[PDB]
Image (cartoon, rainbow over all chains, first blue to last red):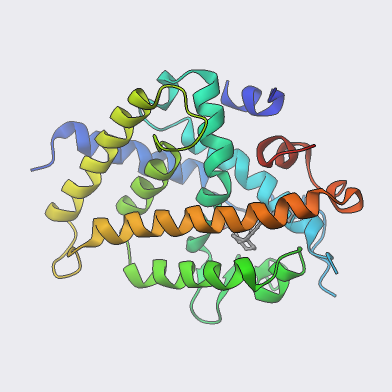
Length: 10
Length: 240
Ligand SMILES: C=C1[C@H](O)CC(=C/C=C2\CCC[C@]3(C)[C@@H](C#CC#C[C@@H](O)[C@]45C[C@H]6C[C@H](C[C@H](C6)C4)C5)CC[C@@H]23)C[C@H]1O
C-alpha cells in the first residue's frame, strides 16, 4: 500500500 | 481557434504550477545539509527529491480530470512520472551559464559533480544534462511547460494503468490544448514541429527514468544508503 501517497492525494 | 475551455485548462495548469513551484530556500534550509566532499550529497538530494514529489502530487491533483481517476490509477501515474516531472520542472532552475541547477546560493547550486555525489554516473547524468540543454533550446512558453508536465503525468501507456481509456481521454484534451496553443500563440518558425519535439522530450524522460531506476534499485539494495532515503521516496520509487 501507499499510505503517504494516498494521504497526499486526499 | 482555442476554445474558452482550452484557455481554462491552461489557466488551471499555470495556477497549479505557481502554487506548487515555490522553492523558498527557507524550505531548503529544512533539508539535511548538502555535504560536498562519496554519497555525501545523497541525504540532501533525497530531501530535495522527497519535497519535490509532494509538489508534483499537489500539481497533479490540480490537473483537470486527474481527480476523476481511481486512487490506483493516480498512484500508478504518480510513482511512474515523479522523477520525470521533477527533472522536467527543474529546468526552471537549470542555468546554461554553467550547466547547473542554481537555486540562489552556492549551497543550493547543484552541478554534475553533486549529482554523481548522490550515487549516479554519466549513465544518467550525460543524457540528463542533454535533456536540460535541449529543453532550454526549445525556449518553451510557461503555458507549454505546464502542459508538458500534465501530459507527462497523465500518460495512458504507463504500465500498471487500469482505466487507460479515461487516462487517454484526459491526455487527449491536454494534447489538443497544447497543439492548438502552439499553432495560435507560439511564434513561427518556432512553432514548427514543436509539439513533436516536446513529445520526444517526454520519450527522453522515459529513458532517463529507466536509467534512474537501474541505479536506484542498485543503491536501494544497499541498506546503509537506503536508510538515508525518506519514507516517501521509498514509497514512490520502490522498496524490498
Ligand atoms: C523545486 C525544484 C527546483 O527547480 C530545484 C530542483 C533541482 C533539481 C535538480 C538538481 C540536483 C539533481 C537533480 C535532483 C537530478 C536528479 C536525479 C536523481 C535521482 C534518483 O535516482 C535519487 C534516488 C534516491 C537516491 C539519490 C538521491 C535521491 C533519492 C534521488 C538518487 C534531476 C533534477 C536535478 C528540483 C525542482 O523540483
